[PDB]
Amino acid sequence: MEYTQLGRIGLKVSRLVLGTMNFGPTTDEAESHAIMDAALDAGINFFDTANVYGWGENKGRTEEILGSWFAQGGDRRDKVVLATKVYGNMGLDGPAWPNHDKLSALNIRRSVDASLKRLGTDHIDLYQFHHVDRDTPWDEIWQAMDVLVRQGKILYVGSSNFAGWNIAQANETAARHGRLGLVSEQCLYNLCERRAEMEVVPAAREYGLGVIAWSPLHGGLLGGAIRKEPQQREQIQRYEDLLDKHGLEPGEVALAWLLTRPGVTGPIVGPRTADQLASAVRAAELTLTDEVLTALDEIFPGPGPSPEAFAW
Amino acid sequence: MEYTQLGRIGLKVSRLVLGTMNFGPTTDEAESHAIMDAALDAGINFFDTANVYGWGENKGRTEEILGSWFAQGGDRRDKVVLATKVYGNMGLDGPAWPNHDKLSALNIRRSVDASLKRLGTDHIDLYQFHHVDRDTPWDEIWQAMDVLVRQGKILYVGSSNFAGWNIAQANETAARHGRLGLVSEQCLYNLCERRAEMEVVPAAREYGLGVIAWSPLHGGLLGGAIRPQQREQIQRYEDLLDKHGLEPGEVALAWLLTRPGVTGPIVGPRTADQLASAVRAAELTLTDEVLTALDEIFPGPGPSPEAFAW
Amino acid sequence: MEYTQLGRIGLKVSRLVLGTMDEAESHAIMDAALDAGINFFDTANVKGRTEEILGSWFAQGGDRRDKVVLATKVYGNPAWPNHDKLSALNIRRSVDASLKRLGTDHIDLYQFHHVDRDTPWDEIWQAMDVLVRQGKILYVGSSNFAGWNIAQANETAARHGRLGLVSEQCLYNLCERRAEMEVVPAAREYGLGVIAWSPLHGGLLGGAIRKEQEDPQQREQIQRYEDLLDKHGLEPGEVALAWLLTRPGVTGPIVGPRTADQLASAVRAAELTLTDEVLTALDEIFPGPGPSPEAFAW
Amino acid sequence: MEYTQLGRIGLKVSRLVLGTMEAESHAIMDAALDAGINFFDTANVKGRTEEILGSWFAQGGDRRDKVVLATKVYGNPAWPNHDKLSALNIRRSVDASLKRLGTDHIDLYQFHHVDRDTPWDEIWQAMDVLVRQGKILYVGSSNFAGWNIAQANETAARHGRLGLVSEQCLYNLCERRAEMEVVPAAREYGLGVIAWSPLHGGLLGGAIRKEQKDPQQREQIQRYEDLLDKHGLEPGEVALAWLLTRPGVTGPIVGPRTADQLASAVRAAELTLTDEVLTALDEIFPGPGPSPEAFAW
Amino acid sequence: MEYTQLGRIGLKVSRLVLGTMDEAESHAIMDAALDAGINFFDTANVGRTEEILGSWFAQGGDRRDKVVLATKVYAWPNHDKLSALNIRRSVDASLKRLGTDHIDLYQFHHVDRDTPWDEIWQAMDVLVRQGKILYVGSSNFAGWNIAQANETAARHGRLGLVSEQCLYNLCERRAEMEVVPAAREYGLGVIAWSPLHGGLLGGAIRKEQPQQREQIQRYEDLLDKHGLEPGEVALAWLLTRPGVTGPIVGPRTADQLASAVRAAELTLTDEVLTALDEIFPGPGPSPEAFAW
Ligand SMILES: CC[C@H]1OC(=O)C[C@@H](O)[C@H](C)[C@@H](O[C@@H]2O[C@H](C)[C@@H](O[C@H]3C[C@@](C)(O)[C@@H](O)[C@H](C)O3)[C@H](N(C)C)[C@H]2O)[C@@H](CC=O)C[C@@H](C)C(=O)/C=C/C(C)=C\[C@@H]1CO[C@@H]1O[C@H](C)[C@@H](O)[C@@H](OC)[C@H]1OC
Ligand SMILES: CC[C@H]1OC(=O)C[C@@H](O)[C@H](C)[C@@H](O[C@@H]2O[C@H](C)[C@@H](O[C@H]3C[C@@](C)(O)[C@@H](O)[C@H](C)O3)[C@H](N(C)C)[C@H]2O)[C@@H](CC=O)C[C@@H](C)C(=O)/C=C\C(C)=C\[C@@H]1CO[C@@H]1O[C@H](C)[C@@H](O)[C@@H](OC)[C@H]1OC
Ligand SMILES: CC[C@H]1OC(=O)C[C@@H](O)[C@H](C)[C@@H](O[C@@H]2O[C@H](C)[C@@H](O[C@H]3C[C@@](C)(O)[C@@H](O)[C@H](C)O3)[C@H](N(C)C)[C@H]2O)[C@@H](CC=O)C[C@@H](C)C(=O)/C=C\C(C)=C\[C@@H]1CO[C@@H]1O[C@H](C)[C@@H](O)[C@@H](OC)[C@H]1OC
Ligand SMILES: CC[C@H]1OC(=O)C[C@@H](O)[C@H](C)[C@@H](O[C@@H]2O[C@H](C)[C@@H](O[C@H]3C[C@@](C)(O)[C@@H](O)[C@H](C)O3)[C@H](N(C)C)[C@H]2O)[C@@H](CC=O)C[C@@H](C)C(=O)/C=C\C(C)=C\[C@@H]1CO[C@@H]1O[C@H](C)[C@@H](O)[C@@H](OC)[C@H]1OC
Ligand SMILES: CC[C@H]1OC(=O)C[C@@H](O)[C@H](C)[C@@H](O[C@@H]2O[C@H](C)[C@@H](O[C@H]3C[C@@](C)(O)[C@@H](O)[C@H](C)O3)[C@H](N(C)C)[C@H]2O)[C@@H](CC=O)C[C@@H](C)C(=O)/C=C\C(C)=C\[C@@H]1CO[C@@H]1O[C@H](C)[C@@H](O)[C@@H](OC)[C@H]1OC
């Protein structure tokens, strides 16, 4: 297992991030636990979850499954860098009661308290915004997060689905008064969707955030979606054909590709079974030749950074 | 129900603020709870109280009435933005024991501890100065408030009965050391009394404070004389509202909801009927003719310096 | 002559400020204002031509420049964009024009003519700091601000080491006391000198009814004022000025004497002691609103 | 003429920016003055253009006093430090610009492009030297990313300095990707947005009828020209007028070579587009939306 | 010619830095250095030197505009060291001797432990703000002097040291303990003075015909097996070192220039690098260098 610093900070994490969104809705508790043990066994120390995982009327269930996993002891809590999120509506799906979603200090307080109860732990290592909230100013957000820091309830703060300028504004605001800023950004990033390269990833790299790629196979579409059974199909076909030609698995290459991108800490890997985890772990050891990198780049061009992306 | 951001911050509030001053002194606990459930049903999430509500020897009773409401469960606490106040004498009415009113860190400590006990909760969402205290510096006040923020005992700080320059001084002082300053001013504003517009509301807007109008009916006066220079003015008002078939109480509220910078008025119902009426005032549109008429009868000063100079 | 600190700063000024309004006639009161010990000269009308007349005054030598605290103002007054108001652009052009007309290399107190709510204080303080570091200006003052504008301005200045506004020139007199609600409280809090403009309310407090004989309610008021002073042996124009010199935070009124007789009258106004009984009755005739928020709430 | 604040600052500008893209230049600049345009930029829609402004100002008649003068860093294989935004390159470019313009100050000095190799403490040192000498009033950007505006202005504010007051970016019906992050950031930080190539190099200027490329781009332009035929609207005027409806936009740079093109740009600033016309332009020329919603959710 | 950012700043310099050791022949070698694409001129020895540069710019032809001009500071009290007093008199004399209105890189000649940084940055900021100096650099500092200096400048918004000139070559590698780590952390370019250790790595044992001589012998003998010139290799070695901007070279002739230029084009094999590292061990970073 390859390890790296999470951006500029002192925290070392596995290049694979274990996603947990399947634990609860699709994978049962006992199997989720076996996967998490398997993940530790493979050297994966970075586990990602969210208050809202579990979905609909079972929001919170995933956090509860990690809580029962820690409760078995055996140094599980101690070995893991635990990440969860705040922003989402935790009540009935649909329009939220005011201040029961988004990033007011009010929603942060109630969300973190509920997450700590479900996770059965006194601290979260990486507390992440699920999304930018353009209505909440950073002096409010940093007040909320600093209260939790100083109480020992969280260590690090991270972002998810931010724009590049939000990352800059957050970290400049934090730095003004000596606070550690965002340490990581979780953006949608994969061969199909490369527009994070325009500004989100450049900002992250400037400010020393780790970059965590969610949906690394683009919902499945890069995992061998055509062999399984618009003009997007021609790309995918050319993709599989190129990987047939070279003997490589689609699912594994989508992950290995992300590992070659500048600034990228690693992909979120969201296995349903211990078999799919072991595949992810192979993808991490895989080495991709400069020839196959050119090919994928030709099939899946990236925008490049702004302003060059749309101007010069 | 129309919602809005409280000034520049991420908190979203109903444009009606439920005032609780009647809960205890005139409306009773059981009925107060009735009204507060109806306010939730109406989409009102913003509840305003104060330690001194109750009046006389019953000061504190409103806070307790809120406390027993939260104790019923059903996510009542979790659904409200709870706001209370510090400054007032909580002992026997008349001259205060020193440091038992006003805004010394000493009075702030003892006031918040008693409010949290009565309210039956571990935190207040919005803790408001009831009035400006010009004898207490902002480095002292913000120390006291910052202690409460970091302990998780309050989230936001607001003001009430400030001058505009007090708003600027407070928030400039907070911003110097990276603190969130005042998020709202609760000022006396209505058709009769519009001198908040000279400097209070301009200042609040510059600094991104919510503006919450208290005494939106000027203590009943804008409610009815059906039941000397000023009698004449109110007469002209009630006659205008007879012409258009509009309730006086509803227009005074809806008018404040047209003012630039105004979050909304504090509505203080004695009864569930008075509440449903406030909700109706929130739904009212006022024609440009009615707005222009009210402005003639009840002129505003406009901003300083233009208000008295040019 | 009574002298005072201009607010919190180290500059000492006369409690009479010499405002404005022939050339050698102006030079003569100015020399006379000096001999009377008035050191604080302001180009505010009680623009371009007045500066030139000060300019020719200084050009005569005799330590005239060295002896005076020279205050001027952004020119102001349908204008071409940026030829009014307080952009860094307008400030640059107004100051350079003023220095050329005043025929001096520095202005002691450079003042804003009016609040401009479209220009942020980091822009304004940039423009002023350029001039301070070049030595073209010493102190910065306001005119026709709100209390909160004074607060914003001095807080912004103080964040980066800068001296803020040292003075505010506002309309303040027996007739118009609404400066007392917030402007003068803000000024007092931040250590600004308050310079009272139109101290006689455009002449209304200088004995305008007795000068008429040679609005219903306001006339009743002036009439009750002239009669109170008749009763007390006191010149109205002098009492208007003396009243202001009793008010908390007031540096002094602007006066525009054109003769030894008018200068001597302002000087006697500054030496005048109004009795508690006079002050009590003036307060009754011309009530102030008190500070906000007590002024309109409690 | 419609006037606006340049972003958050107190400087008032016309919503048309005269891109000076000698004798026929001088003529059009006087007509722009008389039309109430006070905002003159040396951005091409550099070298000679500045000299042409300099001889304009040397004619006198309060011309320098009446204009907001904006220029740019020159830019350009370059000799080291004769391109980009080192303090060394800024000194030499401004000194040469002041010489050519025959003026002792520039009102708005702009970066020509983001330089990723120069830290903002270096850039702000260079600009603060000039501001404190009086050679420059305001600073602006061109061809920046959203995060570069944020970084610039946070760095400036930290030590009390006025940051960027304006960004010049490529923005028109055809190219709307500035809306992802550049314009959002400019709006957050209170920069004026100045739209260069507002007709996308003539292409929105009725380019298919002046024939009297890619198949899909031509299809798009065709519907545009047909929509405006239907409504009786000049395509050149509409491209400009659409930019004036966009949140955050101060205005477009125009390079009128004739009284006719000037008068046209002036009419565009007075034109009101109906909601139906706005809906239809939007359908033909869709914007990406703000990031992250533009590519995520 | 190879170019690099000077540390973290936006200034681009040649990886060879032209130092100095009559008049029209200095002028001619400077012209030749431009033609080879060297833009970085330093008055440091590898008064009169500044005057020679002055007459060079006085010829015109965009000579001043094409070069990054670096000079340095420098006993009667305050006529040495880094007092605001000596800085002022030294820079005034430099600008006159150099016949220019600005210096691109103004460098301290040595650490002065008796002057605080608030006094030094006052003096530098005055000059930066009058336009007389762009960038500030150090020479012969400790690592902690670099940290203190740049932390002090950052406090009040000011650009700190952009470069350190230290004694660094195969023979003297102790700058690697802390000076070069500090410079790397703070984003200073590292300029290697005496890159040939006074000519000891320039083929000295051949030129003549204790246990230091043993070292130089294994060096010269290794460079015979590979068909490499010692002069060139000591330069190329430094160019492979982390944090190094480049060496100060003082060519007097077109012939030595061309040697310097070749040494910047040269690529040493990992075999050669490994062998140089064996003959000339470095201490590593503190605290590992002396503890663990
Ligand atoms: C002590 C001496 C007397 O008292 C005064 O002379 C005080 C008056 O000057 C007040 C303030 C005036 O009222 C003021 O008139 C100004 C023109 C307004 O100023 C305006 C214009 C502005 C530019 O100044 C601006 O800044 C400001 C905000 O608005 C101002 N405003 C605040 C509204 C307003 O208070 C007048 C209007 C005319 O002058 C109001 C009327 C009803 C009046 O005569 C009242 C008299 C009273 C109560 C007492 C006695 C005599 O009153 C006697 O009281 C005894 C008990 C009996 O003898 C009585 O007889 C039966 C009676 O005799 C007459
Ligand atoms: C390996 C070389 C091949 O090159 C490619 O396969 C590259 C293509 O995949 C490009 C990028 C596609 O064009 C992309 O189509 C996506 C659906 C869009 O993505 C969408 C969806 C989104 C979610 O991704 C979003 O983020 C994005 C912004 O918009 C995307 N956009 C950035 C606009 C757009 O570039 C396709 C559209 C369909 O697939 C465009 C068509 C006209 C095309 O074939 C063009 C050129 C070339 C030279 C093809 C050769 C084949 O030619 C021959 O193919 C043989 C198989 C080889 O062996 C060679 O023969 C020896 C070779 O010869 C040259
Ligand atoms: C729109 C219809 C009428 O207009 C109004 O009714 C407006 C009035 O309400 C004004 C403002 C009042 O004057 C206010 O009296 C308040 C008690 C003061 O409030 C006090 C107390 C406070 C608590 O509010 C405090 O906050 C404040 C600062 O001070 C307040 N102050 C700001 C000074 C002061 O403006 C009244 C006093 C009594 O109401 C003054 C009297 C002499 C008056 O009527 C004068 C002029 C005009 C032009 C009247 C028209 C025409 O009247 C007729 O209207 C018909 C519709 C037409 O067809 C015409 O008929 C022919 C026309 O007649 C020509
Ligand atoms: C007004 C309604 C019409 O809708 C439009 O005309 C919308 C089109 O203009 C879209 C956006 C174009 O697609 C764009 O093609 C550009 C070349 C790309 O731009 C490029 C270049 C760039 C420089 O812009 C760059 O910045 C950008 C990122 O990529 C751009 N990209 C953002 C991906 C891409 O959206 C076209 C391709 C060319 O015109 C795509 C094709 C398949 C298409 O027609 C699809 C759907 C519809 C529903 C058309 C109707 C016609 O149908 C009927 O047409 C009648 C005339 C109407 O009146 C209606 O009748 C009622 C209507 O019926 C509903
Ligand atoms: C490739 C392998 C070769 O390895 C070297 O040649 C490495 C040597 O250069 C080391 C480092 C020297 O030791 C250094 O001697 C300098 C004068 C000191 O420098 C001084 C002065 C300063 C100014 O530099 C200062 O900065 C510094 C701190 O202190 C320095 N210091 C760090 C203390 C000190 O390490 C020598 C002294 C002379 O050269 C010390 C003695 C005990 C010695 O001969 C040891 C080993 C040898 C001979 C190994 C062979 C060569 O010898 C044969 O080479 C053949 C090619 C092969 O067959 C080999 O087979 C393995 C072998 O055979 C026997």
Image: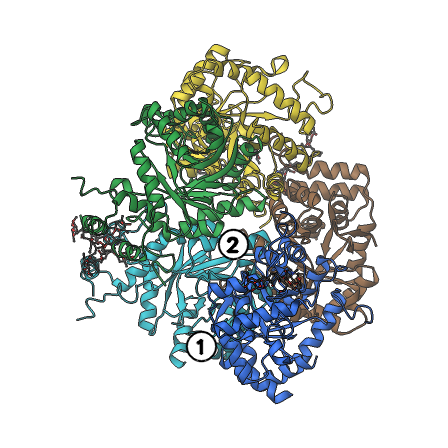
Chain colours: A green, B yellow, C brown, D cyan, E blue
The residue at the point 50 percent across, 11 percent down is: B29
Q: Secondary structure at mark 2?
A: helix
In the image, D198 versus E264, the foreground residue is E264
In the image, A19 versus B203, the foreground residue is A19
Point out residue B238 in the picture as x, y percentages from the top left corner: 44, 27
Report which quarter residue A2 is drawn in.
Answer: top left
Judge: label 1 CB < 8 Å from ligand 4. no
Residue position marked by numbered label 2 in the rendering: D153
In the image, E267 versus A116, the foreground residue is E267
Point out residue E139 in the picture as x, y percentages from the top left corner: 66, 66
N-term mark: 2 or 1? 1
From this viewpoint, which residue is outermost toward the bottom?
E24
**D177 left or right, relative to C213:** left
**Looking at the image, how many numbered discs can be counted on the residues?**
2
Report which quarter residue C109 is drawn in.
Answer: bottom right
Judge: label 2 CB < 8 Å from ligand 4. no
Location of the N terminus of chain A by quadrant is top left
Amino acid type indicated by mark 1: Gly
Residue position marked by numbered label 1 in the rendering: D47
Amino acid type indicated by mark 2: Asn
Q: Secondary structure at mark 1?
A: helix
Marked residue chain, label 2:
D
Location of the C terminus of chain A by quadrant is bottom left
